[PDB]
Structures are given as structure tokens and as C-alpha cells.
Image (cartoon, rainbow, N blue to C red; front, side, top):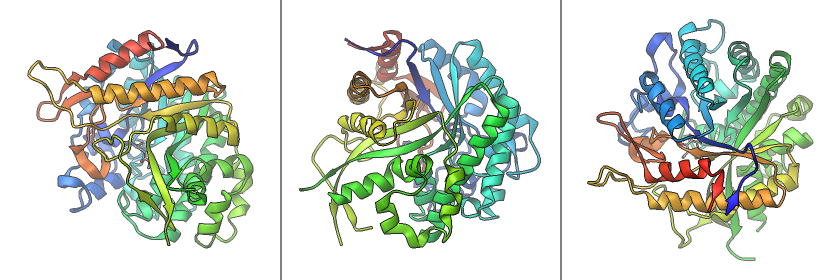
Amino acid sequence: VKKFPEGFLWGVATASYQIEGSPLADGAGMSIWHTFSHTPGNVKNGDTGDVACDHYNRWKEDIEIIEKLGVKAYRFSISWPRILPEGTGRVNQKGLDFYNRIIDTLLEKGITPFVTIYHWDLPFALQLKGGWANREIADWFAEYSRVLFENFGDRVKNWITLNEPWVVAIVGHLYGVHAPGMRDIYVAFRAVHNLLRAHARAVKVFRETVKDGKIGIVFNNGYFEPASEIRAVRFMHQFNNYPLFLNPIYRGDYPELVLEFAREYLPENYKDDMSEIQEKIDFVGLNYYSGHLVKFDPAKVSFVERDLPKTAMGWEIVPEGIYWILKKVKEEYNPPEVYITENGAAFDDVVSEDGRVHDQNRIDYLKAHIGQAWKAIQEGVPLKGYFVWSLLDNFEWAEGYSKRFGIVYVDYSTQKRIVKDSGYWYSNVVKNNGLE
Ligand SMILES: COC(=O)Cc1c[n+]2c([nH]1)[C@H](O)[C@@H](O)[C@H](O)[C@H]2CO
């Protein structure tokens, strides 16, 4: 058997724009994912978040599903433009009401809320003023965060400033594949820097406003292995994984190979902001999905396709990656607490004639990764919790509804939820507090 520590937090994770639908209900402002998904060519099949999982109406049902599965923590995000329709200034009480009902319900049912403040749905009104490219976002973000703390901080005690600021900056502003759909490397790195400053401003406000809770930040991570016998792997780690943000947070500068590549793209006096950026955080969230073979190639790095099982995303399944990144984060920055805030897989799920979804591929994926996280705990990593991405099949960004990551299947024509075998399997893992 592989049992986890007593009080280990088994969770599932979602994001507002991916599940909610009704993006314009009850006075909500438009978000950049509203405007991006409504722009032709940006998202597969013209898919948008207009309806998604209709969680905006079905939230109680979905929470009752979390409850009945015995899952102990729910990670979800708040839509900034539901709360502040223009991003700053006016507060929308109906937006607050929506999340208040979700929060109270979870608490009533003994489920621990983990709130992601920003999971990519920036108010459109602020994108007009430059979004993450504008230094003033540190103030906008801090004022938004202050509102959340004041309203919910009596009940929510676990907070995440940013989901994957690497993706926000690079995929949103260099690759142009995500909202706001830009391709400018100087904008992208100014977004990197500004995300840090906004995160640190929000942590600071948190200490003034919520004196009994905890706050952290979430990073995407890949397990990069070299194609031969390598500095390219060092670069990929420092650029794509937690060091881009943790070196500033813990050591007060960007990682060495990030500076070699991107110094010219960062603001000229960026070190002026580093001491503020070092604001103390309580935990690191790591998201992990995939491993990559990497070689130097005249960013001077390209990927090598390997055999190896892949998911529907074409992501190579490499379970030892989650152990590696867990070990490496302790070794490099030794944060006091770590959570796996997302781990999961997209497979081509089908409802069998028996009415069930027989996702053995997903069970195998989760089991392998849960086992590798168990190992990291035996070897001393302060891992406090683990979150499956995702509770539900949902809007998978530029892929639309075509990629299914849920442990619960959503039939989009009816909004029917069907617990997949992986969801039942995970329930038993949570009940048993580990594997066997
Ligand atoms: C480059 O590293 C990554 O993008 C890892 C990653 C995967 N995922 C996320 N990040 C987001 O937090 C979720 O909103 C997605 O639905 C989920 C699945 O694609």
C-alpha cells in the first residue's frame, strides 16, 4: 500500500471560463477570453465559453458530485470581470453572490476551498489599457485581490494569486495562441515581469487583510530530458518551469539562462522591482502533465518526438516527471509547502452502451503520477495536497470542447454529468488516503 500523510488534501480543480458559461450574466464585464474566442480563427471549431458546462447554473449539482466522491478540496477560480466589470472601481454584488454561494456550500459539506484569483480571464476593459503589458496592472490586481480578501477571506483560507504566469505571458503575448492573442517578445517579458509585481502586491495586501490564511502561486512544469549527452534542458527548466518566477521570488533575480536569452526584452531597470517581488509566500503550487525530449537547435531549443504513450493532446506520458519536479523544487528553493495543483490527462472518452465511461487510460495515468508523488513525500518533499485536472470535461482553451480532461464526463447537448471510471477510482483513492 501507498498511504499519504494524515490530513493530505485530495482535490479536484476547475477554472471559471472553462466551466461556467453565462459570461455576460448579472452585469459581468467581458473578459479577454470572451473577445478572443468570439474572434474567428482563434479557437478550434469556433468554440467559446458562452455555455461551457453551464456551471453558472449547475454549480450545486457539481459540488454535490465533489461531495459524493468524498473529495476533500475544490480548487476553482474567480472571474475578475464578474467581480469588477471594468476591472477596477465598481464592484458587482451579483458576481460576489455567485462565489459566496459556492464557498458557503463547500464549507457546509466539509470541502476545503482553494481559490485561484486569476486563471486567465482578464477583464476586457483592462486589456484596452494594455493588460499585463501595463505596469499599472500591479495596482489593478492588488485592488481586485483586496476585494476578494475582504469579501471571502473570512471563509476562504487558501489562495492562489496566479495560475501559470508563464502561459499567460508567453502563450498569450508571444505565441498568440491564447488571449489576448499577441506576438511580441518585448510585450511577453514585460507581462512576465508585471505578473510577478502584481502577485507580490496581492500577497502584501493579503497580509494586511487576511491575517489567518495562506497564499501561494501556481506554475506549469514539464520534465525536460536531453536528446543526447543538455544546457538546453537547463534553459527549458529555467524558462518553462517554476524558476522563471521562483528565482525572482526567493533570490531576487531571473534565472541565469533566462537572462542570457531575454535580458534585452525585460525592462531596463527591472531589478528595481525585485525586493518587492520577494514578498513571502506560504506555498508553491506545481502543475504537471508531460515530459519532453529536448535538443539544442540553431530560442535555440526544439522538441524531439519520442515513442512513449501520449494523451489526446499528444503529450508524452512520463510519470517520473512529477517526482523529479517535486524533488527539484525542494532542492532549488525549499518552499515550506508544495501542492500539486493540477495533474490529469485528455483521452478520447466514449460513453459505452452500459452508460459508463471506461477510461482505464486515465486511471493508469493518475495512478502512476499519484505513486510518483507518494515517493517524493517519502523522500521529504513537503507535499500537502494533490488536485486532479479536472472535475469536469470543459472548454479547453484554443482546443475548445474537443479535449476532455474530466473525471466526470459532460454530455454538452444535455449538460448531463456521468462519473467516469477514473472518478470512481479516485474516490476510492481519497477514501483510502492513497493507493494499493
Ligand atoms: C504549458 O503548461 C501547461 O499549459 C500545463 C497546463 C495544462 N492545463 C493548464 N495548464 C491550465 O491551468 C488549465 O486551464 C488547462 O485546462 C489544463 C489542461 O490543458
